[PDB]
Structures are given as C-alpha cells and as structure tokens.
Amino acid sequence: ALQQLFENNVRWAEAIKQEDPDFFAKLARQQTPEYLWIGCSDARVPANEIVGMLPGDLFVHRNVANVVLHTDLNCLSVIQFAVDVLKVKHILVTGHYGCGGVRASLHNDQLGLIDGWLRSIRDLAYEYREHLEQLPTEEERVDRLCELNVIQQVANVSHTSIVQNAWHRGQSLSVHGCIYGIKDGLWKNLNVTVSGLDQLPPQYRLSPL
Ligand SMILES: [Zn+2]
C-alpha cells in the first residue's frame, strides 16, 4: 500500500508548517538552488540527506551509475536548466562505492537496455584494464572503477558547450567530483574540480558563439 507514504507526507508537511508556516509558500515563489547534484538512482544515495540540504537547496539528476553523455538530452537538459536558467554555482558529480551499474559494466551478463547505457563505463574498464587487473578483489576493481567513472563524468560535464558558454559569459561555475561510501555514509572529495576553460585540453575547447 501507499498509505504510509501519504501519511508520512501529511505529517512531514505539518511538522514543517509548525516550525515555519511560510516555509513552502516562500519556496514556491522562486527556485534558487546553488547546486546541481548528478548522482546514481541507487536508493542508498539520497542527495539531500547526504549533504544536509533542505528543499530548495539542491537541483537533482539521478540516473543509473551517474552517467553523462553528450547526446543525452535527459541529463543535458537538467544541466542546461541548472546552468542557464537557475545559474547554479556548482555541479556536484557524485558516484558511489559498490555501484551496481559500475559492477554490471565489469561483468558480462546482459541486463537489456541498461547494457547500452553502461557502455561508456565498460569503455573505462577497458582503457584501464592494466590498472584494474593489478587489483586483487572484485570489490576493489569495482570501487576503483566507481572513482574512475566519477572523474570521467566530471570531464564530460565540463566539456559540454552548456558549461563552456557559461564560462565564456563570465558566469562562475565549478564542476566537482565526489564519491559516497554506502558502507560509511561519507561523502568524499575526489579533488578533480574544474572551474574554467583553461583547465580543458585544447581538443575539447569550444570557441565562444
Ligand atoms: Zn549506483
């Protein structure tokens, strides 16, 4: 039944209105998050809770294994809305350890549609086959690939014309790579932050319009 969810909602809404009766009314007027979160759909990685944000703070995209593709208008439209319309200052690319999407990309079972979605991670596993091979346990290979994935996705976001054109017009915008431990609740910085055009390889730089 959906009863408990409806009941949780009515209790939550009422609790907030008791502490601040204008809470939702004020929020509903203007959307002004400083952050966009790009993360995995995994139920164990809820964005707001992990970084203690409130409704209104965090624009969110979640997909399988937090993949960013330059032909995917789903993720790209979230980025473009965030960057062009909301003018978020930060894009938080957050992958996590023990990601099943990353895991699936390391094995050879077919999962259907998802197989094509995860292609780019599978590409990552192949380019780093040497590195990954020198790690003993599958858990280690998976977790390293989770990190490699995040670092790659940070690159992918920063290479978009969406993000470059924000920089061209002097908009302040940083793309961060973080990784969440589902084993310990800790959200960790991979320290791969990109905040300007000068940090991009020449081959990915696009001229202003
Ligand atoms: Zn995941």
Image (cartoon, grey):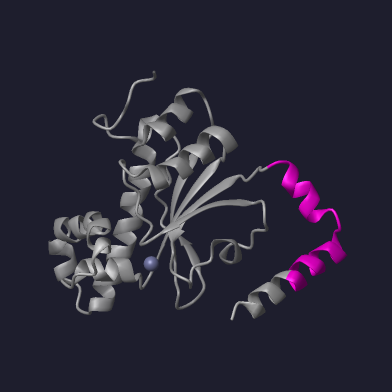
In the image, residue 67 above or below residue 18:
above
Question: Magenta includes 23?
Answer: yes
Kindly indicate the quadrant of the structure image that contains residue 155. Answer: top left
Residue 8 % position (x, y): 70, 75
Q: Is residue 180 left or right of residue 118?
A: right
**Which image quarter is the N terminus in?**
bottom right
Question: Magenta segment, which residues?
Answer: 10-30
In the image, residue 39 above or below residue 111:
above
Residue 52 % position (x, y): 63, 63
Kindly indicate the quadrant of the structure image that contains residue 21. Answer: bottom right
**Which image quarter is the C terminus in?**
top left
| Viewer-proximal residue among 10 and 128 | 10
In the image, residue 207 above or below residue 39:
above
> If the picture is divided into quarters, which one holds ligand 1?
bottom left
| Viewer-proximal residue among 30 and 46 | 30
Q: Residue at x 14, y 62 (%)?
A: 129
Question: Magenta includes 86?
Answer: no
Report the residue that reaches farthest toward the top: 209
Residue 66 % position (x, y): 38, 57
Q: Is residue 173 left or right of residue 96?
A: right
**Overall secondary structure of the magenta section:** helix
